[PDB]
Image (cartoon, rainbow, N blue to C red; front, side, top):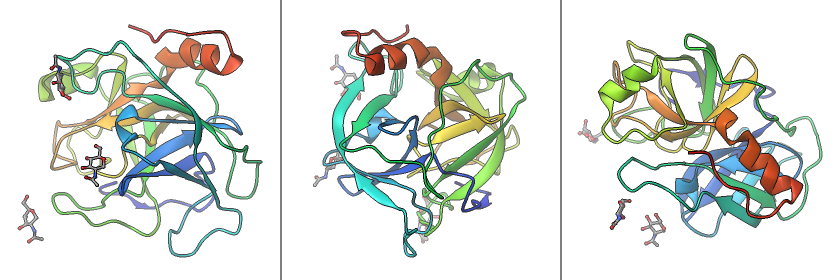
Length: 231
Ligand SMILES: *[C@@H]1O[C@H](CO)[C@@H](O)[C@H](O)[C@H]1NC(C)=O
Ligand SMILES: *[C@H]1O[C@H](CO)[C@@H](O)[C@H](O)[C@H]1NC(C)=O
Ligand SMILES: *[C@H]1O[C@H](CO)[C@@H](O)[C@H](O)[C@H]1NC(C)=O
């Protein structure tokens, strides 16, 4: 996250730290056994850490998990960038609520353009050139008119939200992918892609639009067979 500050230690109980093949991502605990992240974060041998804040001062209740179930959309476009960038993972064992662990559930509605959203992650706080923080950084950004992302980007995927600061300066960045966009207290986005360097004016982040995936998520977790992703 560029242009933010250290998150409050208590404001991200649903935030998962996802490590796969040395690559860093965020994720969101949506109930006691399941995490939503970006499918692009599935880079191999995934370890999912819950209840983490400082990577160098471990919360007493921090836990390590790995995927026991893993789902994503099988029909993805090839012409858009990271189409349907979402992956739903069931953890190997549940994680109970604790000081630093609690799920964030499914949004009741997609967010209005203009809504203030929190972004968060352990991703770089500088761009270009990686500077990885020991603590997750958080910033407030907004849901932007989708046309802003359409103007900034080539093959923008559908089922996405455009979020950032129109003038730049605050943004997610490398290492934050898969992490949540929380707007008005609701889990609305999973970071997929954005501009590099990060936080440029009119080059917002592209967040998979969680609301659109409600049926898919519920279908998978509720056990009814071979759900389908939204168009
Ligand atoms: C679609 O684009 C991806 C980029 O990730 C590339 O790996 C792949 O070769 C493309 N699909 C086809 C039809 O080759
Ligand atoms: C690990 O997997 C990712 C998949 O995207 C790849 O980028 C990376 O090169 C791999 N690392 C190794 C050991 O080559
Ligand atoms: C990091 O990359 C950027 C250009 O992409 C540049 O500003 C810098 O010279 C590189 N590394 C450093 C810190 O010197």
